[PDB]
Amino acid sequence: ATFEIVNRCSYTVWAAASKGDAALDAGGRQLNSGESWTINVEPGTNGGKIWARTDCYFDDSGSGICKTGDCGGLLRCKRFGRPPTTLAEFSLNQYGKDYIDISNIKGFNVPMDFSPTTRGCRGVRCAADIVGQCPAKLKAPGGGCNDACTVFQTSEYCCTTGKCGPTEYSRFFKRLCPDAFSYVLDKPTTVTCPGSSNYRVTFCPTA
């Protein structure tokens, strides 16, 4: 499956794509304002994620650092990135169907639209200004808006026991972006698409 990843932000981002234990495609690449990068993801990819990283420096070998979303200092990500990171999440060809969603469970750094480019389902979007409205205690000094698990490390915020409920913090995410996961047990906003759909992930989809 192809995912066109498009940076409509006014700033450079370094796109990243991983399924946690491996890169997807090259795993990462710089996208200046306006650029598009098309990757190929193997059918049957389960638990895939795509995200943006900000204010990165890499050297000639592709080692460095990112202020949000750093995946162990690599340009070419093999593992998930350091919160805060708005996440495009997907599992492909799962008993005949694709599943897509956007999640704020690991915080928010960059607005995002995640849409099929092929027929038969809708896209999802989290494009509100969550960084500028972020509650004081969630603001990440390095840039972006942390989820409350990252900040406070409690069973309630992290949903460790499997029994958590919504919180003042999760409700800020949900109010700003009703169509993204705000906490682990949030009512699902996952979209069911035809198996083997193709997709576009757009950073900063709106002015």
Image (cartoon, rainbow, N blue to C red):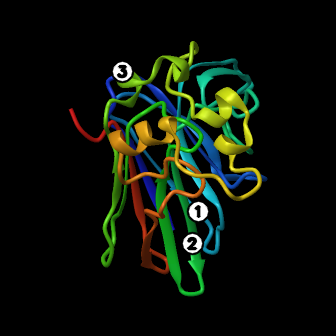
The crowding category of the residue bearing disc 2, from other C-alpha atoms within 10 Å (few below 14, some 14 to 19, many at least 20), is: many
Closer to the chain start, of discs 2 and 1, is 1
Q: Give the residue furthest to the bottom.
A: 96
Looking at numbered disc 1 in the image, what kind of residue is underneath it?
Val
C-alpha gap between disc 1 and disc 3: 33 Å
* Residue at 29% over, 41% down: 205
Looking at numbered disc 3 in the image, what kind of residue is underneath it?
Gly
* Residue at 51% over, 19% down: 139
Report whether 201 appears left or right of 1: left
Label 3 belongs to which residue? 132
Label 1 belongs to which residue? 41
* Residue at 62% over, 22% down: 66
Q: Secondary structure at mark 1?
A: loop
The residue mark sitting in front, 2 or 1, is 2
Name the one closer to the observer, 30 or 108: 108
C-alpha gap between disc 3 and disc 2: 34 Å
Q: Give how far across and how far down residue 88 sits, in percent.
A: 50, 51
Q: Are marks 3 and 2 in contact (CB under 8 Å)?
A: no
Closer to the chain start, of discs 3 and 2, is 2
Label 2 belongs to which residue? 92
Report whether 146 appears left or right of 61: left
Closer to the chain start, of discs 1 and 3, is 1
The crowding category of the residue bearing disc 3, from other C-alpha atoms within 10 Å (few below 14, some 14 to 19, many at least 20), is: few
Q: Give the residue furthest to the left.
A: 207
